Amino acid sequence: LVKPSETLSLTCSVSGESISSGGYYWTWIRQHPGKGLEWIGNIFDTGSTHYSPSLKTRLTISIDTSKNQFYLRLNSATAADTAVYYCARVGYSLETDRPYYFGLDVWGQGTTVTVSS
Amino acid sequence: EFLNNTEPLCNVSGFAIVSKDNGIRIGSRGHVFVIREPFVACGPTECRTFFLTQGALLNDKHSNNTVKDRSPYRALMSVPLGSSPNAYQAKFESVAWSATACHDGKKWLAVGISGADDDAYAVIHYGGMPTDVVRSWRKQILRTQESSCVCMNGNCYWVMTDGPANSQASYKIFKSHEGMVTNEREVSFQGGHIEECSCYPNLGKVECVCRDNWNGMNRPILIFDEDLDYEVGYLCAGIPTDTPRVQDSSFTGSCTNAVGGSGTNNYGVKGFGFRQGNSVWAGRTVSISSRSGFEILLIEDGWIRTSKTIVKKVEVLNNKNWSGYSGAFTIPITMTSKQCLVPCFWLEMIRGKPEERTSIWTSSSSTVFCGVSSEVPGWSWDDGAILPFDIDK
Amino acid sequence: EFLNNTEPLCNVSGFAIVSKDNGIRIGSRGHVFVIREPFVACGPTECRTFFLTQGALLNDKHSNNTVKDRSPYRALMSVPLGSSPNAYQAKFESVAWSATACHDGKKWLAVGISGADDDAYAVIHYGGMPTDVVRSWRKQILRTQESSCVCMNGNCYWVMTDGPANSQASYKIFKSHEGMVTNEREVSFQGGHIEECSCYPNLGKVECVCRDNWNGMNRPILIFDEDLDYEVGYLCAGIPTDTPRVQDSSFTGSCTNAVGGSGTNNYGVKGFGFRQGNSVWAGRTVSISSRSGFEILLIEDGWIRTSKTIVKKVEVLNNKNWSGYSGAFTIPITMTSKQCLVPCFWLEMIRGKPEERTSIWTSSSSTVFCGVSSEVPGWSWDDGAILPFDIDK
Amino acid sequence: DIVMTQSPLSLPVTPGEPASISCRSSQSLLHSNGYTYLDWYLQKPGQSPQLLIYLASNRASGVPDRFSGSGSGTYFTLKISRVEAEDVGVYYCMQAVQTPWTFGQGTKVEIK
Ligand SMILES: *[C@@H]1O[C@H](CO)[C@@H](O)[C@H](O)[C@H]1NC(C)=O
Ligand SMILES: *[C@@H]1O[C@H](CO)[C@@H](O)[C@H](O)[C@H]1NC(C)=O
Ligand SMILES: *[C@@H]1O[C@H](CO)[C@@H](O)[C@H](O)[C@H]1NC(C)=O
Ligand SMILES: *[C@@H]1O[C@H](CO)[C@@H](O)[C@H](O)[C@H]1NC(C)=O
Ligand SMILES: [Ca+2]
Ligand SMILES: [Ca+2]
């Protein structure tokens, strides 16, 4: 449980693979009760980051390659930030002369964050 | 009788032009295919321009989305050196969206990769019939080297790779006798990325100068021989040669480590580099951040010594003109009767939507040069098309 | 020296793609013929795509009625494997509106039926000259297998039929030697229909899997040898493999009797089936009521045992793409140096007015596959033409 | 963002028959490098989502051979050749063209 205007944070872990193996982007993905999915942001193995604009003022997302772990922090959580939070992986690249995309192929189990007193 | 190549590479002093497709210039009215990347390979009777068509002709409506570089419609065909890639003289070779080909003295071997992204496989043609198949092993995009394979004492060799683009992959060296594969050995190389090599034989060792698509401004080298023992490392030169790079005075160079830069780390372009004793004839694009122009540099002791002393420079495109991939090949003894192998290189010039936003298609055109013991001058032998074409209107 | 074929068929584990015409996709601006049905046949030097042109190019006003499948203008022409069926590479072989052709080790043989509906006759060309003529005997539409003939020890064999389409006909087995016919025997088969066979040799017998166009969901089998003794009956498999069919769990199968259906009784499609010991690699469309999508199924003991156990399945077109005929051939020892015959098959993809009502013409495009001992995956190697064409506007 | 809209909010269905769901985006999903970045994902009762189709046309690995995809530009479709009892769930489209990825509204599939 999280109380309003606290800092939410979450831990996601990797195994079988390692972080910095396979060149995936690690993603956080949200789901409010009764609604459809939403996308929070991407980290690459080397720390370059993408954020959804609606949350970009609140967020901070980071890796620790020595722990095979990656992290979400969301400042000033409102009651409306109540959701199931999923973490995933997705391999893709757009620079090269042979692009690819293998969308969100593996999902972790969800965490039901409830933001209330 | 099988083609030897156990003979040294010729010393050369300048590179003279040999052929020029004029593909796009003729294709404005003639029936000419859309090509993303070409290459050249030489048999004992002739040299032939291979290319990966996109199954459609210029100015034809089926050329619309030809920026897309992998699809079930691409095919490898082959046209004799210098003739345009026209619809009626192109001999079909393979179905393929990434290939390699070379002549072993008896018959033409071609390797054509096909199948879906996550499950690709290669079919090894030999004289017009499929003799073997190699499937992915990491089950991401499988790739061959986009230029000829290297045949010696009747065995033909090539490098293939499976895995990420912007991160460490898996790379394997292959070996075939009369089509079918007889050996395969993986390159353990934890510091870098060997994607799109350009290979040539030299006194019994196959040498390859490749494409570092991760954390590097500098060319990886791979050297291997009869039974696939190898050495891996980097082109020591003090002069960087990939497309994204910082200027020559800022780079320091390394023989064993990938040297990265500001904004240069996740991109590159296919090149070549002929060793000449300890010096190297390294080809590179004039601009430091885009595929334009082309230079050939003879760097003294650049194969081993982090030197920056450029002894000779040629130019074959000036910086206002678009260029692209470049690769190596050699013209055998059976042709020239010299007691050594003559080094040659090709250069493609790309035109279309990746830079010229208004055109819908994307195609390229080839120019071919060969080494000459005399000194030779440079000039801008550009592609000379006048876009937009009549289907872009 | 004549081409042997007294050698066993090769055991295969999956089929790898070999070529793809891209005929319609190139024919939009190129000069490409309209074709209804193609096929492939292999000599000792090369394999060639044969096809029955309709005397007119794509995207041209003389294609306004090519759904009409018999006319004086049709002609059989031949192009090396994988090159488009264009106007300037095609070598003329025979005036014909239904034909078969095969290389006997010395020269190409090609049988071209022509003449009016009620009075047709076949011309047997051999090395470019008419050696013999075979006339109708029931005086309705004379027919041949629209796919290669089978040559052994110098003799060449094929199956012809004369008589009704939705009712019992007359079927005959022929045997040439250097062009002219030497022998002829009639297939007595009161229970069924054998229209449009796909034949291949196998250890000195010729095996054909055919097309039941009357009261049958199931393939007829014909097996004959040197002096034309034969066995007739049906592909025992518990899996039905004609186009009109009931689903696999409703069908029961028979080795000797035509198993009909609800609404499936008077129509069909040309197809193939390689025996592999007692199992069969049977090809069939994906849909049970229309010519769309293609599968290849290895059925265990399917050749003899009414079994339904599909051991392997491959797909080469997905169900949203139109398909068509299909047929067997084999690549000889003279090419592969294997001590066994490599099995291969072709698939045609029809486009135009029989299903796409708005276009005026009707043409088809060829894909060719060959068997490989490795496992090989599937994909949707479809035809990719953005119809309608400019002549349709 | 690309606004995503998806036409049946619930689809009644029954085993053995074909079925279809479809999707439309407020700009064409044709990226400048030629590929068309649209996916479909399936969320079964009390589970995470699962990948079905990873570009307009391409099925993912391990997905049963019964699904099929089609479309280009703005309008895309998911086909089920025969529906079977394991297919109940909520189906979302997704697009991966722009820097914010957006999911569809979510078609429920209800057996009848
Ligand atoms: C190939 O090389 C060997 C080794 O020197 C030589 O003796 C042989 O004659 C060569 N053959 C040809 C055809 O060049
Ligand atoms: C190319 O295709 C796009 C749709 O993908 C279309 O907007 C455009 O008009 C087409 N142009 C031509 C010349 O076919
Ligand atoms: C054909 O077959 C016979 C019988 O096996 C064999 O002896 C003969 O040498 C063969 N000829 C050719 C040309 O392959
Ligand atoms: C084809 O033929 C019909 C008459 O049989 C005619 O009405 C039509 O205009 C013709 N179409 C073309 C494209 O010539
Ligand atoms: Ca680089
Ligand atoms: Ca039938």
Image: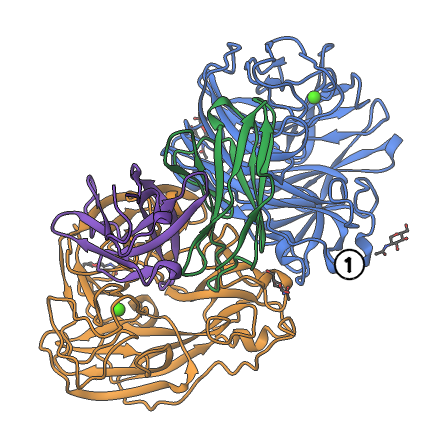
Chain colours: A purple, B orange, C blue, D green
- A54 sits to left or right of B22: left
Where does the image place residue B222, in percent across and percent down from the top left? 18, 61
The answer to whether the beta carbon of the residue marked 1 is less than 8 Å from any atom of ligand 4 is yes
Given residues A51 and C170, the one toward you in this image is A51
Q: Which residue is under mark 1?
A: C391
Single out the residue that lies furthest toward the front: A117
Asked if residue C273 can be seen in this view, the reply is yes
Determine the residue positioned at 49% across, 30% down: C5
Q: Quadrant of the C terminus of chain C?
A: bottom right
Determine the residue positioned at 29% across, 61% down: A49
The answer to whether B270 is drawn above or below residue D109 in the figure is below
Where does the image place residue A3, in percent across and percent down from the top left? 26, 47
Using a 10 Å C-alpha cutoff, classify the residue at mark 1 as few (fewer than 14 neighbours), some (14 to 19) or many (20 or more): some
Determine the residue positioned at 30% across, 79% down: B371
Quadrant in which residue B145 is drawn: bottom left
The answer to whether B90 is drawn above or below residue B346 in the figure is above
Where does the image place residue B20, in percent across and percent down from the top left? 46, 77
Determine the residue positioned at 23% across, 84% down: B247
Given residues C267 and B213, the one toward you in this image is B213
Question: Circle 1 marks a residue in which chain?
Answer: C
